[PDB]
Image (cartoon, helix red, strand yellow):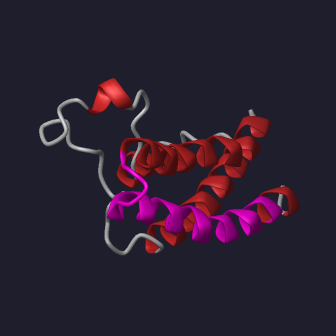
Amino acid sequence: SMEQVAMELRLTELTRLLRSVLDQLQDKDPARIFAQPVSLKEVPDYLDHIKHPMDFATMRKRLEAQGYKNLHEFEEDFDLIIDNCMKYNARDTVFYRAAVRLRDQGGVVLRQARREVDSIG
């Protein structure tokens, strides 16, 4: 059907906007603390602490499979990246502090992304 194709153009355009958002978020992480999953070889107890690990590469795999149906889904995953880090790492750590800074700077990008997704449809 033609409608399925129009929707697919909408998901595709959302994907194009989400890719730009993802790249902008990932620029606020120059240390690359959040680029890849936490290593279960290096933190073997990680899954006892964090039930839903997330990272930017895992978000990117989902994005390229057009696996985010709306902005809310994408934000949920970005918020896991931050929230997992702030739970596992103590307040006085470089990791925790990187997550605060990513959250703060990310908010600005996400605030305008929500306006673009409502505006463009």
Q: Residue at x 28, y 33 (%)?
A: 46
Compared to residue 92, the image places residue 30 above or below, namely below
Dominant SS in magenta: helix
Viewer can see residue 71: yes
Q: Residue 107 in magenta?
A: yes
Residue 103, percent across and down? Answer: 57, 61
Drawn side of residue 47 relative to residue 70, left or right: left
Residue 118, percent across and down? Answer: 85, 56
Compared to residue 57, the image places residue 43 above or below, namely above
Q: Residue 101 in magenta?
A: yes
Q: Residue at x 23, y 29 (%)?
A: 45
Drawn side of residue 31 relative to residue 108, left or right: left
Drawn side of residue 103 relative to residue 97, left or right: right
Toward the viewer: 82 or 7?
Answer: 82
Q: Residue at x 75, y 69 (%)?
A: 112
Kindly give the residue lying farthest to the left in the view shown. Answer: 41
Residue 78, percent across and down? Answer: 54, 50
Locate the N terminus and report the quarter of the image it occupies.
top right
Part of the protein shown in magenta: 89-115
Kindly give the residue lying farthest to the front in the view shown. Answer: 92
Compared to residue 5, the image places residue 60 above or below, namely below
Residue 30, percent across and down? Answer: 36, 75
Locate the C terminus and report the quarter of the image it occupies.
bottom right
Kindly give the residue lying farthest to the right in the view shown. Answer: 119
Drawn side of residue 12 relative to residue 32, left or right: right
Res. 66 image quadrant: top right
Q: Residue at x 17, y 32 (%)?
A: 44
Toward the viewer: 79 or 89?
Answer: 89
Q: How many marks?
A: 0
